[PDB]
Length: 100
Image (cartoon, rainbow, N blue to C red):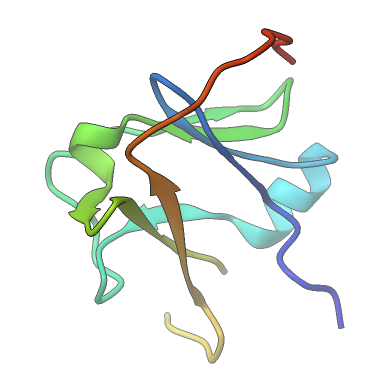
């Protein structure tokens, strides 16, 4: 059975969850939520329909945890297996820049 295919990108100024196609985004319908599955009052996130990306800032859409930040993502009423959590580190290392 298909696994959630969003690719986590922890960037210097945002978090992205990137997809291979707009169809994957529409199928999984990822949304930023809190640890219980509810919307975060402060959080504005963006869906880029051309590049197939969910993106959002650290401060308003993630929670501080040891060593970094946690974001909670709902996919899909609640369904089994509908909650995901991801971690981004506080410290990002940069060696060579290749933005993509």
